[PDB]
Image (cartoon, rainbow, N blue to C red):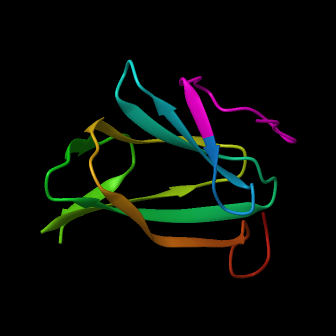
Amino acid sequence: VTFKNGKPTVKGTKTYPMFSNILYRIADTEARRWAFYNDSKELIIHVAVLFDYDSQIVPLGDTTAFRIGKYLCEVDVRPLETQMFVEGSVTGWRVDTLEARTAEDERGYR
């Protein structure tokens, strides 16, 4: 709905908030595509989603996908970034992992 710190690089048709309103799923029904937008200035978010066997999707972008049957797709989303996630026909799905950490290296820079 309302973004505090930036905007996604794409407008789908619907936006769904997800991780205490830091992570948004942007769904585009015409393009049959999902993306994630991270409205934090300070967090890197790792998201993995498990899709049921009858989904017909491909991963987009930097998303990694594995057959697990189910399909596991996962991506990291840096502060104020939009990541393309999957495209195609989604059936059952569920969040498998949703984790965030400060966007800094091990010595504390970033």
Magenta stretch, residue numbers: 1-15
Asked which quadrant contains residue 74, the reply is bottom left
Question: From this viewpoint, which residue is outermost toward the right?
Answer: 4
Taking 43 as reference, is 2 left or right? right
Q: Position of residue 10 (x, y in %)?
A: 58, 25
Q: Is residue 29 above or below residue 59?
A: above
Q: Position of residue 24 (x, y in %)?
A: 63, 46
Residue located 37% across and 21% down the image: 31
Question: From this viewpoint, which residue is outermost toward the front?
Answer: 92
In the image shown, does 68 or 42 lie closer to the viewer?
68
User: What secondary structure characterizes most of the magenta part?
Assistant: loop
Question: From this viewpoint, which residue is outermost toward the bottom?
Answer: 106
Asked which quadrant contains residue 57, the reply is top left
Is residue 78 rendered magenta in the image? no
Q: How many discs appear?
A: 0
In the image shown, does 1 or 101 lie closer to the viewer?
1
Taking 45 as reference, is 108 left or right? right
Taking 67 as reference, is 102 left or right? right
